[PDB]
Image: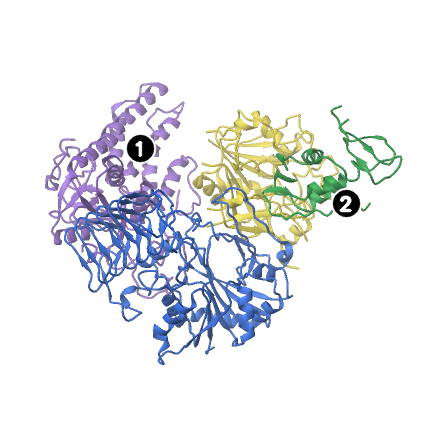
Amino acid sequence: EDRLQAVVLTDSYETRFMPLTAVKPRCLLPLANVPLIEYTLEFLAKAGVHEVFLICSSHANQINDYIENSKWNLPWSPFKITTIMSPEARCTGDVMRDLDNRGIITGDFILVSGDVLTNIDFSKMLEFHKKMHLQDKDHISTMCLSKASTYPKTRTIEPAAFVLDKSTSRCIYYQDLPLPSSREKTSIQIDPELLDNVDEFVIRNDLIDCRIDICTSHVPLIFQENFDYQSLRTDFVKGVISSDILGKHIYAYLTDEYAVRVESWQTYDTISQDFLGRWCYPLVLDSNIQDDQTYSYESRHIYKEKDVVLAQSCKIGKCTAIGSGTKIGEGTKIENSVIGRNCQIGENIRIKNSFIWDDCIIGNNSIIDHSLIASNATLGSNVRLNDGCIIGFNVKIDDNMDLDRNTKISASPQDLDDQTLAVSIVGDKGV
Amino acid sequence: PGISSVIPTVLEQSFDNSSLISVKELLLNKDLIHPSILLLTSHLAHYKIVGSIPRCIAMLEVFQIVIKDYQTPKGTTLSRNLTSYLSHQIDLLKKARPLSVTMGNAIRWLKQEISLIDPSTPDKAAKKDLCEKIGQFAKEKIELADQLIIDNASTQIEESTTIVTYGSSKVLTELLLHNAISLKKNIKVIVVDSRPLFEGRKMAETLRNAGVNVMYALITSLDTIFNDVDYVFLGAHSILSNGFLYSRAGTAMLAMSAKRRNIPVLVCCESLKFSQRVQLDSVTFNELADPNDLVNIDYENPVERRGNKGALLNQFIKERKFEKKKLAMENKPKGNKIGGKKGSEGESKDASNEE
Amino acid sequence: SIQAFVFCGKGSNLAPMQHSTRLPKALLPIGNRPMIEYVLDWCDQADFKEISVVAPVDEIELIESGLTSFLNSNHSHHLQDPKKINFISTGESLQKELLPRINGDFVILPCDFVTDIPPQVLVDQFRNRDDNNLAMTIYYKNSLKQQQFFTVYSEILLDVYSQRDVTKTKYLQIRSHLLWNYPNLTVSTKLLNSFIYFCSFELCQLLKLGPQSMSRQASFKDPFTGNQQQQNPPTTIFILPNETLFIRANNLNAYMDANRFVLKIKS
Amino acid sequence: KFRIPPPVCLRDGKKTIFSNIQDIAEKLHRSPEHLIQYLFAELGTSGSVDGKRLVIKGKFQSKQMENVLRRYILEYVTCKTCKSINTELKRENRLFFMVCKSCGSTRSVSS
């Protein structure tokens, strides 16, 4: 039951975040004024990890530096970090092959794709996995699933329809549809290979992706054997179902509580909002995980760190978090928005449902609505932004600018409009 | 003939005066009853939406329907067995769920109407005029009164508001909705929920259906919710001859809390809910229900978990009892919004003698 | 406002008993008792005064005689024989004919019935939820092949797919517009319809305007789907049928299920 | 008869999608519209022709559709006087009458 190794699939979903991920690594970016890797690490610790393995390729030096700086580098940790360095740009099949070539895989190894933070206890899950394994010899891997918000409507990228069994908890069909975003394909297919064996057919759609996998020693060998499987969800699970190796079982764990993986921008925002509220049961910033953190809890879901300065007569709405070393002026209306560490806010600024990253200067008499500002990118005087406007690294938005809905700004100093240099595109300036 | 005896769970030592038992699933009855009354009774017994205001209206509607359907026998006159029928209906209602003050008033009105027209007139001319009259009455003393109350409230509300609300009182819902839509002020609504009936939840849902900024709380969580917040509104059932607030469950405690934390409470009431019956405690006459309401373990109404509890009769010496109607203190509420615009609760029966 | 229908006919599917002109399917001694006794008992339990019974061109007085002799009810029954039915349509054509006699909501119950479940609670359910059509399903024997398809949705209890496997297409056939709405659907294989039907007022107008009904099962309840385009105007709640599951033994007789009922009885 | 082409169709339903039908039209020497018409006649469907691929309303399969195809290849392709492989389509005035390439005979194409 004890002694389990962890392999984390990092630097995999780059360019998916279309403005960012060009200069700095994907996972190093802060969720709520603190890096996303840390949460994942914490989760792993909670689960039960004895050795840490990270897959790095895109900007690996920085990752290494971070690791060196991190708390787990010191001898007190039960798990040590040793990174896998590989050639640039490859699929999860190739990575698996590489891993196999090296050879550290023992027993029930943990494979996590992307970064996930959830509240559910993992020991019970592990026990379940063990018991099910003990049933039959040819058992493969575990999948994590959670109940969705009644009806699906904000899910277009990954609205997977899971046909599941109640007695065994096993997947029957996997399908992706772009139906709510673009009405072109509205169709559901059922394969007749497993109709006269299951009987209890429950067709469901409202389930959210987690992408946390508890995997047996069979998986890397399988990957080595069948080199056609580049992905792990679309081709692999389906292959398993359609009997590639005959007489084999897979798991689909069902939980009533919240569990969602990071995937896009709106989804990320939603996750952040959830974190701000009391959705996750023990996961709160006021406990202080990174040890340098000095967060404290206040009334009406408001987070305040130490050395946070806010001026008199400023009406605040609901759910606000402020990072350390902030100086905020007078006459501000703040509603459902997070302010980063050491940020300098001017005077008379109306904010609603927005997001502000580490070290950003917000200019006097500006309105920010449902838009994101990345690290070291500054806003000037009189800037009016609309819903879902992503701003990249070190973008200097100077005096007087207006940007419409869903305008994306580049991060690296290419194809998308508005650049890192002085003034965003209303008058042509840049490289 | 009906059904008698056989009651679930323990009878308890304290609070034994009113009916708490009865027909839930129908078996053998008199073959003359109009089914609409039965259906209504079935609804009322297992209702989660109604709260003082709409029940009476529903009853009135039912009565109107009955009148419309009513046919005079060839032998006997219009009023001979009609009274008996009415009595039977009343008995059925009581068996299902005890009669309210509004219902009593309605009954009285009906009786008066019956007395007014003596058996001499033909069928199709009398009831044509009766139903119209009743409709007119309904239009007058209910809807118009409600509208008036709403308008009074409109002028009474100032600038920058933060309100804590409770109940499934329709008038309050109307008020809040009005605030949200047609006034366009800076209104914040905080909702309190209760265990016997999910009224708070319903209110929240209604608010959502409009698009209002909603905080959601309970009876326990009150010490932290204040720490900016000013107004407190409650829904009344009936005001007695004493002046005390004879209303639903979790109101009195809230009022007390409000009193403690500086800012007073405002309650709304109609100009027909007033009673001549004298009582100063909840022990006198109380709406008591079956302990089936306090079985579900949090979250939602339909869940059914096999946790720790699920027995009442087999348990030796165990009393699981809950109350629905309460008597709140007189001095704690300051504002009363009735048919005569504004007034104090200490007036008691100023409208009762006025009729 | 309240009325009940009793459907009577003649056997054609069964192997043996029915060939004689004197003895019809309405009066059969299964175990020293008439088959229609149960229905009468049910009706008595339900408490209703106005009940109209429909009969085909064959046997005009025998049924009446049966009703009269032996049998408790003590109600006023009315029996009619229209001369348009040719057996090849069963009751739909009767329904189409008789319309001015209907005042309100009506209960449909054929002669072929075996019941043990509580009676009034179906009626009450029909009254409460306020829907157009209601049907019931009961499991096949567990004590020691393809049959017919059913689908169930529960959180409200509704029916989605009820098409039989007589002229069955080899792969599964549904609709995604009916699947995207209501995302959760459970496939039933064991359940069978037991001829229990409840209907409302808003059905009388549609029968005269557009006749489409077949076998009282194929297209009696099947036109309900308001998806994709919608061209036919509704008469003035969405047009949806309901389905409820039961545990106790109460079943239908049509095919090779006549000798099993006797076995069930004698224990 | 070996003239029956393999139908490459996935059972992703709601609307019957036949992308391989062009090949069928080609091999059997047929206009695509006639097949569609036949299908319509067989079962109550409504759709439109698209250049190669079909959008036909209904969740139709690859076995009952296959059966239909087989049927259309036993009373709408085969001859009588002489059983031959090559049969071409000609619009001959409104009702369809096809001709055989081997001999040249007018056959009834309606049932």
Mark 2 vs 1: CB contact within 8 A: no
Chain D rendered in what hue? green
At 32% across and 32% down in the image, what residue appears?
B83
Q: How far across and down, in percent of the image, does residue A332 sit?
A: 20, 49
In the visual, does B36 lie left or right of B133? right
Residue located beneath label 1 in the image: B60
Amino acid on which disc 1 is placed: Leu
Q: Given the current orientation, which residue lies at the most extreme right position? A: D81
Query: Residue B83 shows which numbered tag?
Result: none
Alpha-carbon neighbours of circle 2 within 10 Å: few (<14), some, or many (≥20)?
few
At 57% across and 41% down in the image, what residue appears?
C39
Chain of the residue on which disc 2 is drawn: D
Amino acid on which disc 2 is placed: Ile
Chain A rendered in what hue? blue
Tags 2 and 1 both on a single chain: no
Count of all numbered marks drawn on residues in the image: 2
Q: Given the current orientation, which residue lies at the most extreme bottom position? A: A75
Q: How far across and down, in percent of the image, does residue A209 sit?
A: 46, 58
**Closer-to-camera residue (D25/A124):** D25
Chain B rendered in what hue? purple
Query: Residue D4 shows which numbered tag?
Result: 2
Disc 2 vs disc 1: which is toward the camera?
Answer: 2
In the visual, does B246 lie left or right of C258? left
In the visual, does C127 lie left or right of D86? left
In the visual, does A149 lie left or right of B164? right
**Closer-to-camera residue (A228/B47):** A228
